[PDB]
Image (cartoon, coloured by chain):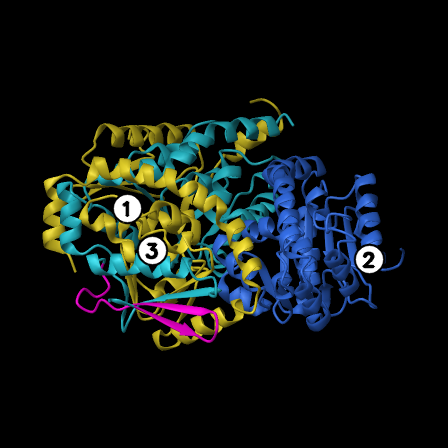
Chain colours: A cyan, B yellow, C blue
């Protein structure tokens, strides 16, 4: 056996993956032993928590080279904001400078957004008295999370990239001077993939956005008009 | 690009840079920037030699949104399933990733109710490095756990991140030195074990019902992506050449 | 009933609802429950405010069910939907800022989470501590915690019922602003002033649109939480935990 089961205290079960030969890749052995380990847990209602762990410097390695090869062989005022979104291939919004209002929102529709620490970012629609447009009300909560989006959108405040970074955004935030160079490097790493794989994957990741954006725009239009 | 407000630059053969440079309007949406941006993206759509686009502004301006004039006009009204083992387990599961988590092995741990990473270890959803699309429910569990935006980069680029890099990017997982990871998992597990089993299972069932309900449709969509991407000679050479 | 909530009109368009049941440290006494409802009804009947600031006193934001209150649910005399405090900030037409200058415990933490803006104090303690008493989270915690803090952190928060300082949450990466306690209310006031720069109708229209999925989805989750309370609340060992661990 390549999975060891260790009880800790009364009701804790540790599942320790130890396929040293394969560094916890999914050999036949690790696969079978993992399934049996979870089946054993399922048959035992003493346990209240499971610790799944690896050994040494390996948690789990994924498909072995031969297992991947087996699969390979078969054994196994209404448009511009969404330009990035409708683009077939990945778009990096390298916002080396300020992104204000619809300019910010336009960039938020890119697959990868990079900010600059010194620049100003704002969904400032409500500063003019208007409810937000250009799909702001959809793309802000979707990229920045529901809670930060309520603040951004209700208040239309201005944040430096450095503020957003301290608030916890998922975007890479860099000094202005480094923004482009980081984007070109990331673009180079992206271009190492087959173009069909990039498009196939982006189509699947952004389908709910492409599907739901039109109705959000309609609701945003109805908010104007009131 | 016509109005001369958007410059296209090819970087290498497969990367196009769309640079917005309406200096007069500081990259606000003037007529020219609008038409030039639409023309730039149409150019991209009709030139599928590119694999990535970089959209950028000039100097201190990315894009300034509606013009002041435009906005005033409006105001005025003139215009075997290894991957789901942790998810199907009735009790809370802690993935103590004291070591590297690579591809399906990373994804398998992300289905746990609590994930802990090591600072020193490397984590990657590396499917796309081999040319094929992510499987094992990655395109569901990675955005579910790490948020839509970070998951885009992780999945599309198949990058390697130390636990310390993810901790800097803002993950909700606890990240510790390798040598503390298991001790902390055991302390957490002992705290969970203070609860009645029935309350733990009833609550897990409720918290993860929408994952158990949705995962099978996502797996189906990932299979559909694998049919389109897995069975190309290019995938076989990347597996032979780039593995470990 | 009748002086455990103070209402202060802080400027022409800003109202502060301050909870100050000192006897119960802002646990949900009958008096606190009644005054909070009354204060939100007053805001609903006077449609001139643009922002509400909900805050506590000294070191307490809100402490959740009183011990007696919890034991009545345990006995099956009541259920947590009997008085609906949990959703006051969500049902409010205008933006609500939860200025949590002090501790936020159980139903008191969750009630604050329904506000449109949440500010935490670094040195205060926050916890969805339901499970520590052996029963499942109610007050809509299983909806609002994952909504505001993200699926992954909510798992831990809800399952383990652990206590976090504001500093701990800040470190774990929450989208809420976390401040020294002494700065929390002034910062709430400043943000309320920036909110009060917008037209009231615009703020109401936008909040209605932003919180519509929450107002639509909450009632089904509350029903599921009532079902979990049916399976978990009325055990003897819950009474033992309430009696043994409260405080």
Q: Position of residue B58 (x, y in %)?
A: 35, 45
Q: Which mark, by number, is residue C102? A: none
Mark 1 near mark 3, Cβ–Cβ under 8 Å? no
Q: Which mark, by number, is residue B108? A: 3
Residue B50 sits in which quadrant?
top left
Q: Bin the neighbour count of mark 1 within 10 Å (Cα to Cα): few under 14, some 14-19, many 20 and up.
A: many
Specify start and end residues of the magenta stretch as a single range. Answer: A4-25
Please, which chain is the residue tagged with disc 3 on? B
Q: Is residue C67 above or below residue B86?
A: below
Q: Position of residue B63 (x, y in %)?
A: 42, 41
Who comes first in sequence, dot 1 or dot 3? Answer: 3
Residue visible at 71% across and 42% down in the picture = C91
Q: Secondary structure at mark 3?
A: helix
Please, which chain is the residue tagged with disc 2 on? C
Q: Position of residue C246 (x, y in %)?
A: 71, 70
Residue visible at 56% across and 30% down in the picture = A220
């Amino acid at each position: 056996s390549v999975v060891e089961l260790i009880e800790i205290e009364s009701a804790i079960i540790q599942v320790k993956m130890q396929d040293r030969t394969h560094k916890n890749a999914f050999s036949q052995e690790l696969t079978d032993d993992l399934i049996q380990a979870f089946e054993y847990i399922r048959q035992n209602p003493k346990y209240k928590a499971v610790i799944l762990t690896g050994y040494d410097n390996y948690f789990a390695s994924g498909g072995t080279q031969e297992g991947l090869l087996r699969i390979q062989q078969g054994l196994t005022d209404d448009n511009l904001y969404s330009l990035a979104l409708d683009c077939e291939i990945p778009v990096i919004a390298a916002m080396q400078g300020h992104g204000i209002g619809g300019g910010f929102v336009m960039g938020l529709f890119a697959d990868i957004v990079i900010l600059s620490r010194e620049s100003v970012y704002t969904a400032n629609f409500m500063k003019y008295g208007f409810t937000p447009g250009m799909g702001a009300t959809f793309i802000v909560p979707k990229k920045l999370g529901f809670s930060l989006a309520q603040e951004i959108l209700l208040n239309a405040g201005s944040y430096r990239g450095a503020d957003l970074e301290k608030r916890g955004v998922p975007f890479k935030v860099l000094p202005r001077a480094e923004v482009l160079d980081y984007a070109v490097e990331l673009a180079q790493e992206l271009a190492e993939k087959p173009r069909n794989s990039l498009v196939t994957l982006k189509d699947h990741l952004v389908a709910p956005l492409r599907d739901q954006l039109p109705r959000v725009i309609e609701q945003e239009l109805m908010m104007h008009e009131k």
